[PDB]
Image (tube, rainbow, N blue to C red):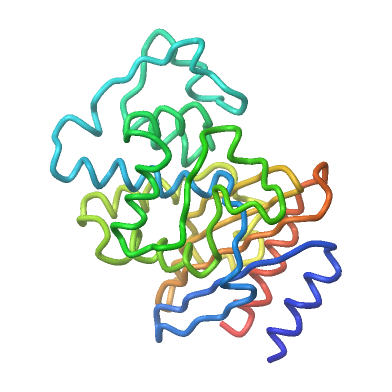
Length: 261
């Protein structure tokens, strides 16, 4: 296709490795590029953690409003929300919101710890039929994004299929599904990534991720005004450890794959 060639050309120009999975829920068609190759998820992994917490909340009434203490020693880099709540503490819902909307790293760690560790997030992914996702480490260690390292990786297609199940399908109960969508729609960090490549009439809920090796990621659910939803994952990584983020690559990739409507 011209789409396959244009993505290959975007990839070559950018000096990295690009991974794309678009799922069109109108007809279930997929548009894939390196769709079955592993990429470091970085903070896009926060979506799976939040969904695991939401799932536990379906049967356990001491989850979403359970208050957790935030110790000064808990704080890691990129924690703009949790760093302001040392005295107040935060609920698991508030931590989930902070992780998703502000990419708060300490919030993610608290969620991982509450669930029982990184393996428990993998276990949640397994429970929804995602046999690819793996979470191995905590924040910020999981952002190393070393080429060839399988730690804290998934494939663009696996992540798209899972994001679909979680936001549009049957992985969560209606109340929880709706909550996750609301959180994603309120993301504060996604303006220059997938959303930048899409029409203004398409509503977006997304989660970005950034890591070492110039790793620049975004996953989105997309709601057109007059068409059925789309699910889009754009992953990008580079050969040099110190490479700068390239959000414009994700916007350009989103544009290529959605251009035909």
